[PDB]
């Protein structure tokens, strides 16, 4: 029972396999079980301006009537410019991570200003933004999608580009708060066997598991590759959906349970 | 290879369990630290210790996820840092917050010889899932910082001599053989507990600058002084960063 | 009138008895007159985990439908561990006060995460958290009970333990905001003539005044003793109720006007 | 007995009414402070003065409680501190916030010779009830800090020579006899106004380190210099902390 | 189209007349089009205490049922005292601007504490305080009227008094958020040909343009003179109304479209 | 005339377009700055550059007002400042935030020789209306600060030699004549683009202390060193502040 776990927590190191096994038996509380986390792509959507953002703002305003939403923003082209300047100077991943956060904050600010008249705030601490998420008149919050790691960012095996960016930031929030759904809003219909902007005979994949994606060695940069490993270790969010936000009503359809785009499963 | 931001910096991580011993362990450590101030430019980072176990016990009983537990444990490391900094205040040492460590350490180490901070990294609610115990703790946070800065060294100060083949305070006490030297890859392949986070071994695999880390006993006066001079007084962990 | 007070405020020292008497004649505005302040014990409740906290969370969720609540948290055993480490080093009360605040913040965070799905936020500035307290869907806030004194903590006559901790922190907030009720949720039915964990023939006290408690030299550490002196000087909250939070429905009963536990009066 | 955190620190509290005199009083005080910078490590704390009386007048007219008035008056002391710090900026002096004074004073006094802060304690909405006038004001805040740090001294700089038996600017002007020396207990038993908070006398009763506090006239150049050297140039208040 | 503007934004200096002309053709989004900004005078109202503030608090509570309000506070006599002390020391306008902000914050705090029981919060970031402004139970926020310039305050041609104070601070917020109305609540019925406290035969002006005010060389310190130049350059708020807040129901009447006081137009 | 708060300060504004060139331009500038640290007390302020144009392009396409665009562009100047500060971290230089620059610059420049900040002023949503492009940008912010502090000088570091009669990279390249010296009033009467904000010319008209500002080419090593010594190596802009 809890008596064995408390004894192990006091006397053993946290690296002890016996303690780790006992902690895994603990109850599982979902903080925000009825919320859906959505990531609005930085390069894929916000950077495209009015033609992409304005229709999505209308879908969000309509969707929040029936769905509790946590809307995270991507970073995009200004972050890529910062990363190339800083990488050329030999600055470490930890410095680049801080620069990237500023770009996701700018994107959340622009989106928040278009949503302010509808009562949707830009927040810090989305998962615990209990008041806006409990009101039918609000039911949504906007947040910056970059993780808070800053200088403590785990670097990649090679290079200085932070490997955990806005896809990981939004996913981990869905995971930590025990949300019911995670939707990535990008500019491609979903996953293809080859790059849709490069190859000619790339076939569409409606559903795939992380294992199958790894086994088939997919050349699809639609999702940050470290997000796939996080998905396999996840306790709450065991599948994600990638949709094309440039198609009118696609986010509305995904929230309604339609199988638009690609579904990526943990197993 | 990325540049070293603060190549002259020495980072020292003090285990939370060393602090948990109170005045009997803290006063000789403070006295040894005072004597080190004119010799090195130090970033002193504190661990969490037993109070993080109590908050994990309550938090797990309430069913809270790993991202909820991470900042709760980090608070304990922050409190140890305020206690240590207060003991060294008369020498010009203070506790600095994570945003200050991340963006303004250089100016703070120009004003004074050492600063104290929390060794926990600010992963918070964005902690990785998998275990119900937060994986990125004090040893990992101290290493990530030391390697990001390109620091001259990282010394881990524990309540034991170094790494043994088994827990020297556990049921297998008699089977515990001291390891004077090891590698991150060798420890990673092992089962059994360690006095360092398992995530530390993972970040050491992708390290860019720190070639070695020494784990020393902070309960034996003089070992920290010796370790900071490169003397072999505990367990040396090779990171797998090859020198020139 | 106000003409004499304004003249005295300009020309006399604030220590002047004439000025002090005139300031005492000023009108009395209650900022949050319909709210009830509750203190959830740190050692007495939150430290006990699921068995104590989960039933209280259900009572809070049910109670906020009819009562505006400001829920403060205690600190408990992790604060006692910090106090013994720091006292052994000879650190002053002012340093210990800052360490204790961190423990009350951890407790407010844990409680807030269990309440987030019900719309109840963890706040800074509870008394002025006007928006959550005005909504029927919310009607409650969680706050950390430690006072903000930090290094400026008034020390006790002897020793370095801060004398104003989470009982004083919650009480002063009830007092400053002119709240209608102050309830201390602990793990004892109330006040006894002797310690209920020590003596065998300790009799229960349903109602007592601060003067009578002092005159009878009570050995009951149920309430921080400096809170009794604050209660005697209070302008708004002239009585407090101590209830056992381990008894199901006790907080609900106290909010309904039932005389469960002990009532301590200023006079 | 608790340890002294900053035993080498000298704390000076400048009365808000001294600042209220403007350039005629501030410029000679600034010039005297400039000359003191190489001699001492100073924490300079400012009081509130007349603007706090105006905000009390409006606030009391609106019926606001004592906890509402406390931070409103404290803001005036903070503004006096920004004015004083700006006058000493060319010497490396700046205003520091209460969180910085509480946790990082040591590093700030290692960088520069003096810093300025608000003397008001952060009691805010948790101010004690009883009086409609906040009891924990600038003299009290300065003393609580000085005694918590175990500072070398605390000097209170007023617009009068020291403590008199009655207000030297009040109706009983002619009955006002100067007190060169007094004790916290003797003043506490007295009725009548004082140029120091009544709460100061209460905290002096439980003091751990500060044995004496001197109240000097900041309108007479040289008195602050002399007081910081321990010379008797105003009223000495004995706290009741007995020396060895 | 947007193609020419994007090319000019990349290749030309921002001072380029061609770029400036193209940027002026961009769409115009109003962030908070249904809100009214009101400035409550510091010296003119709040400094007068209970007799002036209490009736206005009642009007605000009644008015928010039908009007979304952003209520800014002035600074008043404590700021004038700080300005004279600092000016006498030769401190620059940038330092005085920071001192003045503290006085407007004190005034917002006092007003917010009288409004807390009605659900109206004191905020930072009024224009983006989306949640309180979207709820019928709230529909108003209080903010400090000083602009954020601090040390970067543009000084006046002569002297160290900051030329952009709380009238400019509230006006610029109305302008930036695209609000529908800007009302200045002072202690005079409106604009007069001469000073109403000095001259005897000063005639009342119900409506005037900034040009006419400049041409007639008006000696009316009712509005900060730099606000008149900001009004002429404004894109959203092309007129302001000055009302006497000491007359019962005057703010209610102005919100109802009554032409109480003076209307100042940009052209 | 207002007093000079930090008369010994030298302010340098580095254009965002200089930073946009990356390592080829930043590394020689960093090397030149390192050599200047022992010679001057510097406040280094960075501009925004091309990324502010991208955010203006997106922001204007969304129809956002001028007060919405101002903080978005300012963020780019802040990011350039973090990049520059990281390159000088080993010398004790860090990035400081606007509240720290405004109230605590003196203490920070007592600890270390230079600090980096964002040149953008915090006008934010209170930016002036009139143009859809924020008028108070990096040159203006740097000048307002330099003049408020009463700094010894302000040098603007650009990707061009100085001010020409027309854009030297624009369609009228051939008509562009270099101006070695000009006045704020003369430039204000001109039409055509400038490499400095038009608002800079307006604030120079009401300046209290800065008599001249020099615009130099940061792509030519040594010019910044020379400009800080008062040598004429770019365009001198007279502000219209007459000396004694
Ligand atoms: N293989 C091992 N070798 C050495 N010590 C071990 C080993 N396995 C477990 N331990 C135990 O780990 C203990 C150190 O505890 P732990 O590492 O959790 O404390 P800490 O480092 O002070 O805490 P924190 O990580 O919060 O700073 C030792 O006292 C020892 O009992
Ligand atoms: N017994 C007394 N002895 C001396 N001065 C007295 C006495 N009683 C009252 N006073 C008055 O107190 C005045 C000082 O005012 P006060 O102490 O309020 O100002 P301050 O200390 O500058 O303000 P603050 O506490 O905001 O810093 C003196 O000028 C004198 O008129
Ligand atoms: N009259 C002019 N003289 C010189 N350069 C000019 C002139 N008019 C335009 N320019 C252009 O201005 C460019 C400098 O660009 P800009 O001033 O926007 O950059 P910056 O100063 O680095 O940016 P920021 O203001 O963000 O710091 C020069 O490269 C040149 O092409
Ligand atoms: Mg360890
Ligand atoms: Mg006094
Ligand atoms: Mg330029
Ligand atoms: Mo940030
Ligand atoms: Mo932020
Ligand atoms: Mo924002
Ligand atoms: Mo913003
Ligand atoms: Mo915001
Ligand atoms: Mo928020
Ligand atoms: Mo933030
Ligand atoms: Mo942040
Ligand atoms: Mo933050
Ligand atoms: Mo907030
Ligand atoms: Mo949070
Ligand atoms: Mo938080
Ligand atoms: Mo919020
Ligand atoms: Mo801080
Ligand atoms: Mo900070
Ligand atoms: Mo931050
Ligand atoms: Mo900060
Ligand atoms: Mo922040
Ligand atoms: Mo957090
Ligand atoms: Mo805090
Ligand atoms: Mo906090
Ligand atoms: Mo929190
Ligand atoms: Mo938290
Ligand atoms: Mo929170
Ligand atoms: Mo909040
Ligand atoms: Mo906070
Ligand atoms: Mo706080
Ligand atoms: Mo705070
Ligand atoms: Mo907030
Ligand atoms: Mo507050
Ligand atoms: Mo606040
Ligand atoms: Mo809130
Ligand atoms: Mo909020
Ligand atoms: Mo700060
Ligand atoms: Mo701070
Ligand atoms: Mo704080
Ligand atoms: Mo801070
Ligand atoms: Mo805080
Ligand atoms: Mo700070
Ligand atoms: Mo406050
Ligand atoms: Mo502020
Ligand atoms: Mo503020
Ligand atoms: Mo406030
Ligand atoms: Mo306040
Ligand atoms: Mo507030
Ligand atoms: Mo807020
Ligand atoms: Mo703030
Ligand atoms: Mo602020
Ligand atoms: Mo702020
Ligand atoms: Mo907030
Ligand atoms: Mo905002
Ligand atoms: Mo914000
Ligand atoms: Mo809010
Ligand atoms: Mo909110
Ligand atoms: Mo900061
Ligand atoms: Mo700050
Ligand atoms: Mo601020
Ligand atoms: Mo701060
Ligand atoms: Mo602030
Ligand atoms: Mo902003």
Image (cartoon, coloured by chain):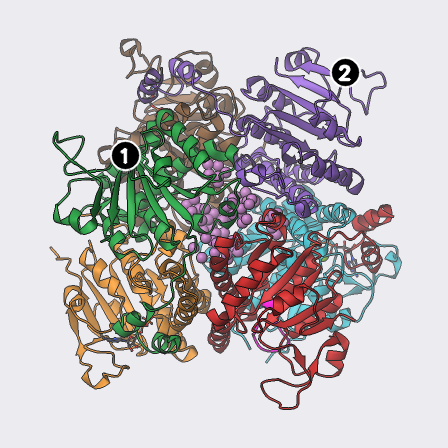
Chain colours: A purple, B brown, C green, D orange, E red, F cyan
Q: Nearer the viewer, mark 2 or mark 1?
A: 1
Identify which residue, D85 or A235, lies in the foreground.
Answer: A235
Residue A6: x %, y % from top left: 33, 20
Task: Tell which quarter ligand 1 is in.
Answer: top left
Q: Is residue D24 left or right of residue C266?
A: right
Q: CA distance from mark 2 to mark 1?
A: 58 Å
- Let me know if residue E165 is in the magenta part: yes
Residue A247: x %, y % from top left: 80, 30
- Structural crowding at the residue carrying mark 1, measured as other residues with C-alpha within 10 Å and reported as few (<14), some (14–19) or many (≥20): some
Relative height, residue C98 to residue E102 (above, below): above
Q: Which residue is mark 2?
A: A193
> Numbered disc 1: what chain?
C
Determine if residue E178 is in view: yes
- Let me know if residue F144 is in the magenta part: no
Residue at 18 percent of width and 66 percent of height: D188
Q: Is residue B197 left or right of residue E46?
A: left
Q: Which residue is mark 1?
A: C81
Relative height, residue B42 to residue D174 (above, below): above
Quadrant of the rendered structure where residue C9 is?
Answer: bottom left
Over which residues does the magenta segment extend? Answer: E156-167
Q: Is residue C114 left or right of residue B156?
A: right
> Numbered disc 2: what chain?
A
Identify which residue, B183 or B83, lies in the foreground.
Answer: B83
Label 1 sits on a secondary structure element that is helix
Identify which residue, F154 or E16, lies in the foreground.
Answer: E16
- Structural crowding at the residue carrying mark 2, measured as other residues with C-alpha within 10 Å and reported as few (<14), some (14–19) or many (≥20): some
Relative height, residue F48 to residue A30 (above, below): below
- The quarter of the rendered structure image containing the C terminus of chain D is bottom left
């Amino acid at each position: 029972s809890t008596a064995e776990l408390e004894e192990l927590l006091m006397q053993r190191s946290l690296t002890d396999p016996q303690l780790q096994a006992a902690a895994a038996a603990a109850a599982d509380f979902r903080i925000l079980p009825d919320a859906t986390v959505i990531k609005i792509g930085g390069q894929s959507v916000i950077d495209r301006g009015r033609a992409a953002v304005y229709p999505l703002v209308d879908e969000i305003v309509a969707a929040r009537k029936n769905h509790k939403l946590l809307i995270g923003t991507g970073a995009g082209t200004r972050a890529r410019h910062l990363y190339s300047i800083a990488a050329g100077l030999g600055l470490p991943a930890g410095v680049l991570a801080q620069l990237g956060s500023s770009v996701a904050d700018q994107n959340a600010a622009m989106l928040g200003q278009l949503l302010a008249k509808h009562g949707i705030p830009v927040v810090g601490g989305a998962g615990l933004s209990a008041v806006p998420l409990s009101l039918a008149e609000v039911n949504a919050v906007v947040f910056s999608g970059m993780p808070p790691y800053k200088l403590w960012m785990r670097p990649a095996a090679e290079g200085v580009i932070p490997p955990y960016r806005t896809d990981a930031g939004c996913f981990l929030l869905a995971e930590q708060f025990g949300c019911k759904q995670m939707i990535f809003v990008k500019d491609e219909d979903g996953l293809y066997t080859a790059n849709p902007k490069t190859s000619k005979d790339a076939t569409f994949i409606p559903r795939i598991s992380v294992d199958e994606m790894k086994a088939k060695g997919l050349h699809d940069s639609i999702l940050e590759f470290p997000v796939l490993d996080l998905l396999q270790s996840a306790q709450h969010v065991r599948e994600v959906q990638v949709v094309n936000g440039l198609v009118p009503g696609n986010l509305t359809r995904a929230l309604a349970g339609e199988h638009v785009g690609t579904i990526i499963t943990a197993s | 290879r990325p540049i070293r931001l603060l190549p002259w910096l020495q980072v020292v991580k003090i285990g939370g369990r060393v602090m948990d011993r109170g005045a009997d362990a803290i006063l000789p450590l403070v006295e040894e630290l005072r004597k080190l101030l004119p010799e090195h430019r130090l970033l002193i980072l504190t661990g969490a210790g037993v109070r993080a176990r109590h908050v994990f016990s309550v938090g797990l009983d309430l069913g809270l996820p790993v991202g909820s537990l991470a900042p709760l444990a980090a608070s304990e490391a922050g409190q140890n840092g305020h206690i240590l900094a207060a003991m060294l205040a008369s020498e010009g040492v203070s506790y600095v917050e994570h945003p200050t460590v991340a963006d303004q350490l250089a100016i703070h180490l120009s004003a004074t010889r050492a600063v104290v901070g929390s060794a926990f990294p600010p992963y918070h609610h964005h902690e990785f899932p998998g275990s119900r115990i937060p994986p990125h703790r004090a040893d990992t946070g101290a290493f990530l910082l030391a390697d990001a800065f390109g620091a001259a060294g990282l010394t881990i100060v524990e309540n034991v001599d170094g790494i043994y083949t088994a827990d020297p305070n556990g049921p297998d006490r008699g089977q515990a053989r001291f390891l004077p030297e090891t590698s991150a890859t060798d420890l990673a392949k092992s089962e059994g507990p360690l006095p360092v986070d398992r995530a530390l071994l993972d970040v050491m695999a992708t390290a860019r600058h720190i070639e070695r880390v020494q784990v020393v006993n902070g309960l034996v006066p003089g070992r920290l002084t010796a370790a900071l001079r490169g003397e072999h007084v505990g367990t040396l962990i090779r990171t797998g960063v090859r020198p020139a």
